[PDB]
Image (cartoon, rainbow over all chains, first blue to last red):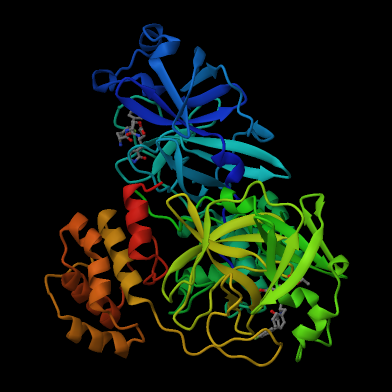
Length: 304
Length: 304
Ligand SMILES: *[C@@H](CC(=O)OCC)[C@H](C[C@@H]1CCNC1=O)NC(=O)[C@H](Cc1ccccc1)NC(=O)[C@H](N)Cc1ccc(F)cc1
Ligand SMILES: *[C@@H](CC(=O)OCC)[C@H](C[C@@H]1CCNC1=O)NC(=O)[C@H](Cc1ccccc1)NC(=O)[C@H](N)Cc1ccc(F)cc1
């Protein structure tokens, strides 16, 4: 029993992290086979911030202008190209520690693990959700760009995020590993705003199931509701509408606990309208929305 | 910016995890050089658990009663012995992935990362604190015994915890890697109770500094206090006394924010006496006590 913010083991990703330096600028890269992927803003200076001419900046760069180090050991760059907002540096040594991997794009509300790195050295691992406004509430400092987010599906590492920037509101934005931003963001220093965020309803319901599995049941009465009645309340509290698909994905948790999905919706409706009245659920005094149904299963079942 | 529950990168520990089977009973082991360490209750059956006579059980077994697997490769056992509550199985091959390591015994209030494993396969990593009552609030299912906790100091893995059992209250108990339990617990299935738990004051103060660094400042007041005055309030609310060494460990956070520790104590005193009033600190409606001053520095400064 117990429930924690649990990340995937990070070893397979740690072995792929490198440092990329161009001029005075250093950030992280992801070394897979004979290519290093990193944010293309490594080729910028301060003069280029508002309107970087990335093609111009890259044409002026040779392979020798890129300094790639793995564990502070230099790899030699033998080619360079741009894909969207990512630079792809071909190196003359393939990474013998490359895991089976895929590049995936995650959907809003889904979670991933982030390996926070500085100067090619991993600092820590934590769990993040892609918010409905396509930002993440990460933990990143200067030097962290090129850190990646990932999930492990079976034995495949599914890379889904590469870190690029922090908005003034303290949230984070980045790309998939093909260099396309999540959300309405660009890698130039225009003033950019995220949309109003909302609460990920299906994930709150999943977390309430995790509480029931762990014995924290005080919020469970034998109440039930309809999907439409629940959504009329959810919207008053800035919760995402619940669809029948979301109901379907909660099936395994409903199956384990014996609590129908719309009964849990009724419990959540009561928690929203009346509050938690000083009580905690799974150690939190707020309703938590960064655990997916799969996250709860995997933690409450022991998948490896 | 940002602040998450962040674990250490787990790759150096992943390479040490093995599966140990004795008859029908399987759990995890830690493979370092040519020794595998695991909980000694692997040698037990149902009737042993009231009062396992572990010396008898161990001496009557042969090396061939132990099946150790690193992935799918079998490691032949060439000796078996017991140190306190840990079994040491000498194997015929040294682990080629053995990191620099130490076995350390951590003090109450300190944090560590847990690599939760099943059948020798890592499943996830999360951060834990040793509670003042010498239990941990972990996330463990059947098959997780032998999972370890650790910190990474420089490039040395400091192993501090190996998982053995769950108390009826839902909290967890285990040993250091010398096989000595934290707290008064024993590896017998008997009614065992943890003493009252208290809140780790120095950690709450570190988390309030993390909040200020991240721009949450509403709870700051203009007052100061003394260690003696504050400690009268701490004991009213079941907080651990604050020591001068705790004040000094907070100095790096005081230096970064310009808020004296005793000023922060005065702010915490008001939070304990009035609560939060439907406001939040770092996205929580409770005072969080599982981040040490170092965890905040390491995260808010980018230690790798
Ligand atoms: C990574 C840059 C790096 O490591 O390379 C050289 C050391 C860094 C990460 C953030 C710093 C602090 N916390 C972070 O998450 N990113 C930047 O500094 C980023 C560079 C950039 C990226 C894309 C367009 C323009 C500049 N700059 C910023 O994050 C600041 N906040 C400026 C900014 C940029 C874009 C916005 F929409 C708002 C604000
Ligand atoms: C690990 C055991 C394992 O993997 O062996 C393979 C068959 C497991 C971990 C707990 C399972 C569910 N969540 C956990 O954390 N440990 C046990 O099952 C443990 C075995 C044991 C260990 C030491 C003395 C006696 C039995 N048994 C228990 O944890 C239950 N809760 C019984 C118990 C034991 C000791 C106490 F103080 C209170 C309750």
